[PDB]
Image (cartoon, coloured by chain):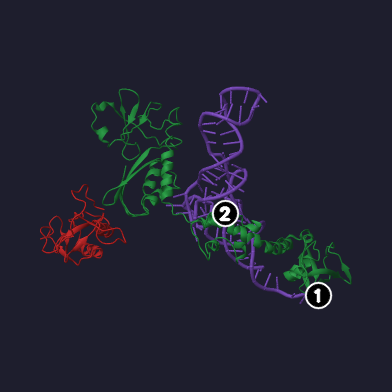
Chain colours: A red, B green, C purple
Amino acid sequence: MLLPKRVKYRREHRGKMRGRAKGGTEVHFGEFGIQALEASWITNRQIEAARIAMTRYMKRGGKVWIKIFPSKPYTAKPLEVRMGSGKGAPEGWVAVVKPGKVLFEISGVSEEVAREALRLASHKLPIKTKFVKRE
Amino acid sequence: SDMVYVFTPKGDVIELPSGSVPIDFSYRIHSEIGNKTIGAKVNGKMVTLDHKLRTGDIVEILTSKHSYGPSQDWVKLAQTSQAKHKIRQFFKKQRREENVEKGRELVEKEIKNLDFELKDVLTPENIQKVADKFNFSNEEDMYAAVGYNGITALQVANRLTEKERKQRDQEEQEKIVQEVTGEPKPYPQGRKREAGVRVKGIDNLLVRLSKCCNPVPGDDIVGFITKGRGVSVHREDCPNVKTNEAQERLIPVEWEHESQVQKRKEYNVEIEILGYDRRGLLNEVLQAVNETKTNISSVSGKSDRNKVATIHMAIFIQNINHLHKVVERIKQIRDIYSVRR
RNA sequence: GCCCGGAUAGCUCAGUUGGUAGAGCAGGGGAUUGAAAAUCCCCGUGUCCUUGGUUCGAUUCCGAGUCCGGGCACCA
């Protein structure tokens, strides 16, 4: 859980996912990165399962460079409750991910590792991925 | 000559050990002959069950068909012990045959307060999971284990509790590391110490083990002449021993494995371990140290965000041959990157 | 006849397909007494059933007995 420590507001509107990425559009702090190809929400649960499968395959990680962060929260009601009567309590977290956003990086490990490394994390995200080198 | 060579109602020589009554004559032929024997006839006359056979006799048996059975009087009417070990099971397999019942109520008594507290298996097979270590040979023993206590249950009921996950129970053994603080309390009032740090060939001098880093046979160990209160054996290649003002106070001393009896009880060896954090890992690193001749004094361990655990073993080890062998005993799992001290 | 496992402190019981060994109680150690109980604490205190055995240590692995625990056979 990459939890923010103290947030100005407990709850936000859910936003609309149109446009390209503002930044994070090209890998530069590593040499083997992963751009998303679609747009949805990503949780801390979808980073814990992401970050674990990074280092189980590499067995000795240089760095990981997790770019995105779950800034925006989200709420839902307790179950079986009629509509209205207040926005619910905050439940999890959401990293807001535009398409073409560099998600992770790989620092200085070979291609045949990296082609298999980001493979094993792509099946933990709800987004189609592709493999981008440093330019 | 320790055996009787008696005759069957055909006339075949029946080789049995000596001293046999005609009850012992039955079980060489078949066991159910003993189940159905009433009387005996040797050479015209009936013979009593109080008769003991001799070598070269024709023994006829008064046998019921399937009607009659044994008593308690016959249990010492078996002279020959190998036939009596059949008699040790003959009267058993009709009394214990009843006692499968009192077995069955009391075998299934001892389960659910120890095993089916948490398992709750119906139809049960966990009580029949001891069909791999014990010679059951059929289901009679697993149900009548307490009916005679030849199996002596709470051994086999502990085989029911053989499920040893023990993740919190190692934290209970981490609480044993909490409760063992008091092993330094035998280091007031003196400790059984030889001249173990030989001071430059000169013995019987006041030295102490350095708490900056522990003096072990890696790099050589050097005694610093202090202002007083002892002499510290600083274990050269230390940042404290290297930055010394007044280098004359350093003394090249010996670790003294060259004597008659080596130091059997060296201790206070703290070990730095950098391993990758996964599950089922922290107990097994404690488990290879478990059953190894090594006392554990402090378990200081923590893992980072990226799950590479920084753990420490302030443990006891006695020799560099005891150290470096046990140093290559934290590496049974290969998740661990490196080890330091 | 047959095969299949246990042959572990004083006693209970953990070591188990290979790290010589724990734990509990009992018991002992002295403070204090006629000695106890009470109070103060300390301590394991083992032919791992033997015989052998492939050895660069075996309670366990193997055979060989013995022994315990079994269920199948063998009807004169």
- Residue type, numbered disc 2: Gln
Considering the image in quadrants, where does the C terminus of chain B appear?
top left
Q: Name the image quarter holding residue B12.
A: bottom right
Relative to C29, is B31 on the left or the right?
right
Mark 1, other Cα within 10 Å: few <14 / some 14–19 / many ≥20: few
> Is there any visible trace of residue B247 in the rendered image?
yes
Chain name for mark 2: B
**Dot 1 lies on which element?**
loop
Mark 1 or mark 2, whichever is nearer to me: 2
Which residue is drawn at the image coordinates 11% and 57% (left, top)?
A23
Q: Name the image quarter holding residue B293.
A: top left
Q: Name the image quarter holding residue B316.
A: top left
Taking depth in this image into account, of C76 and B166 the one nearest to the observer is B166
Q: Which residue is mark 1?
A: B11
Relative to C33, is B14 on the left or the right?
right
Which residue is drawn at the image coordinates 19% and 50% (left, top)?
A9
